[PDB]
Image (cartoon, coloured by chain):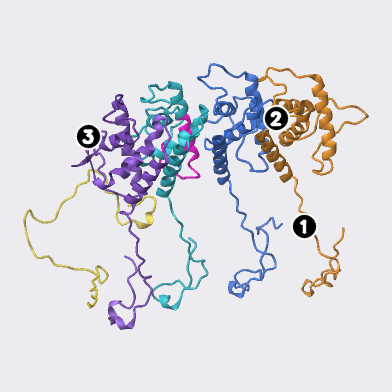
Chain colours: A blue, B cyan, C purple, D orange, E yellow
Amino acid sequence: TVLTKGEIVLFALRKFAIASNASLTDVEPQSIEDGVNDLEDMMSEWMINPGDIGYAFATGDEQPLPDDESGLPRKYKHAVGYQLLLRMLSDYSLEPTPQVLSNAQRSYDALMTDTLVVPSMRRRGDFPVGQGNKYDVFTSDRYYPGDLPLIDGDI
Amino acid sequence: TVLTKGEIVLFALRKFAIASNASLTDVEPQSIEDGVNDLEDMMSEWMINPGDIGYAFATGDEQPLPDDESGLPRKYKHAVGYQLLLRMLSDYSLEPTPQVLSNAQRSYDALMTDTLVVPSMRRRGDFPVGQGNKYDVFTSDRYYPGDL
Amino acid sequence: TVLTKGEIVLFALRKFAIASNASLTDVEPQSIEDGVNDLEDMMSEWMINPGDIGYAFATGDEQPLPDDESGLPRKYKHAVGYQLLLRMLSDYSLEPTPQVLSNAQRSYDALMTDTLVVPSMRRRGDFPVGQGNKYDVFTSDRYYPGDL
Amino acid sequence: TVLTKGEIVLFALRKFAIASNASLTDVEPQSIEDGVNDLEDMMSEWMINPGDIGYAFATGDEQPLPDDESGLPRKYKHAVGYQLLLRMLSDYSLEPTPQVLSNAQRSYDALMTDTLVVPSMRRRGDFPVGQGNKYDVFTSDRYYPGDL
Amino acid sequence: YDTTNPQYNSVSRQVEAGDAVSVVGTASQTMKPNLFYNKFFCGLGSIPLPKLH
């Protein structure tokens, strides 16, 4: 239904065969709690470089739990899982094969595509407005504003 | 035909000889569930970069099943299977061979060729319309709208 | 002699010595039906990039049989067989060889040289017609029709 | 929450498996003391090139303790931990893996991105101000100040 | 009969199911009908054809 902080840590640790449903050896729950903490710190530092994506942080001072819902869309779980796996691979003294790196790169590019900006720079501010715009009757001003016009806030 | 979600996972498993008749190996139930979940996640992700291809997702409580219809045409089966195989081989810690990579990239190139649209630029909006267009009685446009 | 389906599958199996008439150990029919299904999907995909080569897809709802008539011309046999062999070798955990790759490339080029079209660029539609063509004033023959 | 100094050292040790539950190895108190001292010294050195990032130093001629409060936001935790791990690896006679180096580089790049300046240099100081600015009725300056 | 865009109504009520209709005329009568129309009812035009070489 909804994405939870537990199933991301289960997509990780299974995409690299560390632990799985069919595995005869399972990882201790302390490692899952550590993975949840690592995920929270990762999404906390992602607040600056890739921007906000919709993470639901643990409001207040209470400790996070793996059963909380994160609110992320189902179309963002692959990139997050691959990045988290890349981060936690060194914990178990492993190395990433090139195919895993390629998949992670593709997922990261897909995620970064969806959050484009293209600021589309505005005019200068002293740029003249031509007589063709009829600054005498149509628009009172005769130069480009350089700021958002309003009705009562008036800067 | 219907091309159920179960068929796609079985194709990927048969390729690379993880579970096939030639290998004298039968498929475990858990691997099928993992493959179906990975297919669901991959097709949910594919809604942005490649585009929409008409795949049908479950409603409410998902619980996707191998007997559920997929809605994909028969053409995209090979591309979807190869992409799933590439994203799933890491579960069993297997390095793909170059031939599989070439097949996958060729099928993906064909898939992206099928759904390619090239946008056409339009006039600025203040661009004049010449006197040859008869903008007196034939049209009222002294300039192109050109923005939509 | 019509080129029925399954004959292509048998040819692909023979050319890599997986199974043939002289093999003491043969392959189960499940592999053969998997091969014909793979051929069906490959033709469905080929309906996009190479083009249409007159393949006779199965109608209704019945699955493709290994004995029905494919309807392909004889000249495309090697091309289809080599492409199927390339897309099928990975099923048996095997890797191709340079000579097979060269043969497949040559056969594919021979197949592709038949579908070539090289479209011609018509007139712009605003291009004037020379006055020496002796047009008619009221029939709008002063300019090329362009398209449609 | 609070991110005490003991959180950083344990994270740094765990990330290379010096002492973690997965490795079944318990932590040595001497390693904790050395890690705390190294973190304090590294922050004191970071007070020049990366600039202040909100660290809460120990005062009163008292040695740092793990139970104390670092005073840093959780965003810098990964970068600080990776840097400290890189500066402590030589103590145990180890060699970093390329993935660890890439992760540390990415975290440091994010940290540097978060603290950009771009000072945006001012005018000269003897540069004239145009007559269109009305430098007497509306302004008292005929030249750009360009100072302080 | 549009209930969302009442501007374009051209009839008093909707033609619901079960309404009674009728056909004007006779079973197999034939005749030469008279015609009445407006200037802008239908238009006629003749396309000129191109010369051949």
Residue that numbered label 3 is attached to: C67
For mark 1, name the chain: D
Relative horizontal placement of residue C101, taking residue D73 as reference (left or right) = left
Q: Nearer the viewer, residue D28 or D145?
A: D28
Residue C97 falls inside the magenta stretch? no
B95 or D103, which lies in front?
B95
Separation of residues labelled 1 and 2 (CA atoms) = 39 Å
Residue D108 position (above or below residue C93): below
Disc on res. D120: 1
Q: Residue at x 38, y 26 (%)?
A: B20
Alpha-carbon neighbours of circle 1 within 10 Å: few (<14), some, or many (≥20)? few
Q: Is residue B12 above or below residue C55?
A: above
Q: Chain of mark 3?
A: C
Which residue is the site of mark 2? A60
Q: Give SS at disc 3.
A: loop
Indicate whether residue B46 is drawn in magenta: yes
Mark 2: which amino acid?
Answer: Gly
* Mark in front: 1 vs 2: 1
Front residue (pair D24, A64)? D24
Q: Position of residue C128 (x, y in %)?
A: 37, 77
**Both on one chain, marks 3 and 2?**
no
Sort mark 2 into few (<14), some (14-19) or many (20+) by Cα contacts within 10 Å: few
Parent chain of label 2:
A
Q: Residues within 10 Å of mark 3 (few under 14, many from 20)?
A: few
Residues in magenta, as a range: B36-56
Per the image, label 1 sits on a secondary structure element best described as loop
